[PDB]
Length: 134
Ligand SMILES: *CC(=O)Nc1ccc(NC(=O)C*)cc1
Image (cartoon, rainbow, N blue to C red):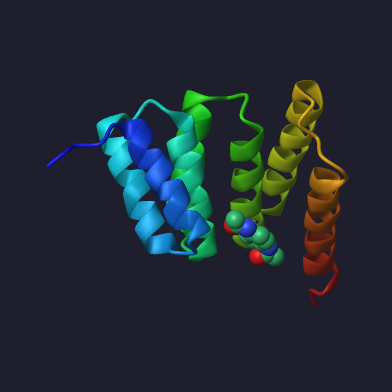
């Protein structure tokens, strides 16, 4: 047999993700991480798998690790913020989305109104959660 490289495992996971096989993709990214745990994008990609599978604590842990390895990552701040938003950690989520936005502008990766839209939605969900209380 052949043992694929971590990079090959990441690409295989990407094809599994494109194939909408999210548990399988997550496991493949996990094999990539085992082969080389110092590459942030393996964790961010697996985090997105876990968000598609609504496995929040696993996504959260992966976003934290990705950001330890690449503190400049637009994607990992965005996914961290999305995971926090879904766990109703609103203020943390918003701050991570604002950092994703600022990093994206700096890197010229701010596409359309995407991250500002995520920020508006996060802020409105936070606002609704307070406004709806008795
Ligand atoms: C390749 C891939 O994952 N594409 C993709 C396209 C559209 C969406 N949008 C929604 O699910 C709303 C997700 C993934």
